[PDB]
């Protein structure tokens, strides 16, 4: 019906449909089509070389969908069908909220970048809870079969106590997640990034971990903190210190950037919001490299930001990522980008003498 070529989607289908629809409508349609399974079932069969064991789980391949694509947990099964080794939904806030006024998402095709200022539009914990409960046992089997689920938590715009927002997310969605993400790095909620500060972070994560440890064993997720690419060296040292002090299970590195790298060409480069895609790529990779060294390679990292190829994935893995995610590449290349990243990553691992993804994790640090 629509299956299923790399060049066709990249050269013809995606540029045409982008020319027809504003970015938010395009996203909604993508979510709808994905959730109905109106995609080719990915033809790439994952080799054993791509398997990774981390965070108390087996991951059939190390390529996941980043938070923000499926904010409300509507397309999880369709995303596994697309070939992702793991799915992260969210960010989800405790109460439903509409997010920022439109327009709030912008394409920069000359930069293969996106700028967004959604501001945590979210159906809320209760809606997402029911959505996930309706397939909880199916997810238990997928997880067992190497396809884990992450749930990314945010906070409401008008909440007084941020820590109580994240605590409520742990209590409600923690029992449905293989891992939870404390998202303290959205650039689109006022004051949120200040929660990355040493004292605020320590207090917030102590409470998050207390809540998590009170869940029954079979419903007890790993806890990860998702961080910005715009941190000072001091901020990064402080995060690494808190992570090790508290026994945080992992880091997601990185969210979108509020910087605007010299050289951006897109007409919309000066829109407010987080920048994603290719201009973020090496900034994200360098942040992974730093965080890996500061945590002595002992804290699993999910690397994210501008991944659109096997080389992009492998650079992050060698810099210290155990797993990678992508989002923005999907908006330019479409669904075929997933098999593309996996096939190229496998070829490059073979070319560089690695036995598998596991041998490559942090390899640059051992040179
Ligand atoms: C439109 C859009 C919405 C996003 N929403 C979220 C979100 O709700 N929570 C989150 O932690 N990250 C969010 N992100 C960030 C992505 O998860 C990822 O960290 C970032 O876009 C870098 O990856 P990419 O270059 O592959 O897109 C969003 C990104 C985009 C482009
Ligand atoms: C039939 C079809 C049309 C895709 C919608 C278009 C024209 C662009 C996709 C697109 C975008 O153009 C933009 Cl800007 C965003 C933010 C998103 C986010 O999901 C996005 O998916 C299928 C799309 C997909 O399967 C994916 C690749 C998931 O978007
Ligand atoms: O909802 C959003 O605005 C959003 C959240 C986030 O974590 N990152 C992002 O780029 N946008």
Image: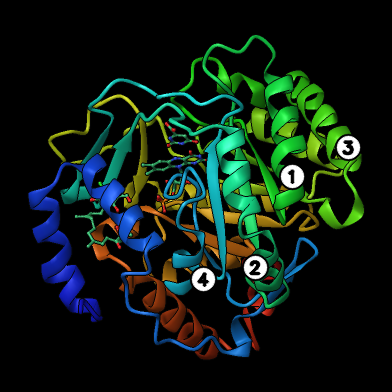
Marks 1 and 4 close (CB-CB < 8 Å): no
Judge left or right: residue 341 versus residue 168: left
Horizontal side, residue 277 vs residue 111: left or right? right
Q: Nearer the viewer, mark 2 or mark 1?
A: 2
Instruction: Give the image quarter of residue 7.
Output: bottom left
304 on left or right of 3: right
Circle nearer the N terminus (2, 4): 2
Q: Decide: few, some or many residues near mark 2? Use Cα within 10 Å; few <14, some 14-19, many ≥20.
A: few
Residue 362: x and y, percent? Answer: 67, 66
Asked if the residues shown at circle 3 and circle 2 are in contact, with their CB atoms under 8 angstroms apart, the answer is no
SS label for mark 2? helix
Q: Nearer the viewer, mark 2 or mark 4?
A: 2
Choose mark 1 or mark 4, whichever is in front: 1
* Mark 3–mark 4 distance (CA, rounded to whole Å): 30 Å
Position of the C terminus, as image quadrant, is bottom right
Residue 186 or residue 229, whichever sits in front: 186
Crowdedness near tag 1: few (<14), some (14–19) or many (≥20) residues, C-alpha within 10 Å? many
Q: Which residue is mark 2?
A: 138
**In the displayed structure, would residue 178 be above or below residue 234?**
below
Q: Is residue 316 above or below residue 343?
A: above
Query: In this view of the protein, can residue 363 be seen by the observer?
Result: yes
Disc on the earlier residue, 2 or 1: 2
Gap between marks 1 and 4 measured at Cα:
30 Å
Disc assigned to residue 174: 1
Q: Nearer the viewer, mark 3 or mark 2?
A: 2
Mark 2–mark 4 CB contact (< 8 Å): no
Indicate whether 319 appears above or below 46: above
Asked if ligand 1 lies within 8 A of label 1, the reply is no
Disc nearer the start of the sequence (3/1): 1
Q: Are marks 3 and 1 in contact (CB under 8 Å)?
A: no
Residue 314: numbered disc: 4
């Amino acid at each position: 019906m629509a299956t299923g070529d790399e060049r066709f989607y990249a050269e013809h289908l995606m540029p045409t449909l982008q020319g027809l629809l504003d970015p938010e409508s395009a996203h909604r349609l993508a979510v709808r089509f994905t959730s109905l399974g109106l995609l080719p079932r990915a033809r790439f069969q994952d080799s054993d070389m791509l398997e990774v064991r981390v965070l108390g789980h087996k991951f059939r391949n190390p390529v996941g969908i980043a938070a923000g694509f499926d904010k409300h947990g509507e397309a999880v099964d369709g995303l596994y069908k697309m070939g992702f080794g793991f799915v992260e939904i969210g960010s989800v806030t405790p109460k439903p909220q509409e997010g920022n006024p439109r327009p709030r998402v912008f394409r920069l095709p000359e930069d293969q970048a996106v700028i967004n200022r959604y501001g945590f539009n979210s159906h809320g914990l209760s809606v997402v809870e029911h959505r996930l409960r309706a397939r909880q046992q199916k997810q238990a089997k997928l997880t067992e079969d190497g396809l884990p689920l992450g749930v990314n938590l945010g906070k409401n715009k008008t909440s007084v106590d941020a820590a109580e927002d994240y605590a409520e997310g742990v209590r409600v969605l923690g029992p449905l997640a293989d891992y939870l993400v404390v998202n303290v790095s959205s650039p689109n909620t006022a004051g949120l990034r200040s929660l990355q500060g040493k004292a605020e972070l320590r207090r917030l994560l102590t409470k998050v971990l207390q809540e998590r440890d009170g869940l029954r064993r079979v419903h007890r997720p790993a806890v990860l903190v998702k961080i910005a690419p715009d941190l000072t060296s001091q901020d990064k040292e402080d995060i690494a210190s808190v992570v090790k002090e508290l026994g945080i299970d992992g880091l997601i590195v990185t969210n979108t950037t509020v910087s605007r790298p010299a050289g951006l060409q897109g007409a919309l480069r000066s829109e407010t919001g987080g920048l994603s895609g290719k201009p973020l790529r090496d900034l994200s990779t360098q942040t992974i490299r730093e965080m890996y060294a500061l945590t002595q390679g002992r804290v699993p990292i999910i690397g994210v930001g501008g991944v659109s190829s096997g080389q992009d994935a492998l650079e992050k893995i060698r810099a210290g990522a155990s797993l990678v995610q992508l989002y923005t590449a999907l908006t330019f290349w479409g669904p075929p980008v997933v098999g593309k990243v996996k096939r190229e990553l496998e070829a490059l691992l073979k070319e560089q003498g690695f036995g598998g993804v596991t041998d490559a994790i942090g390899a640059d640090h051992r040179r």
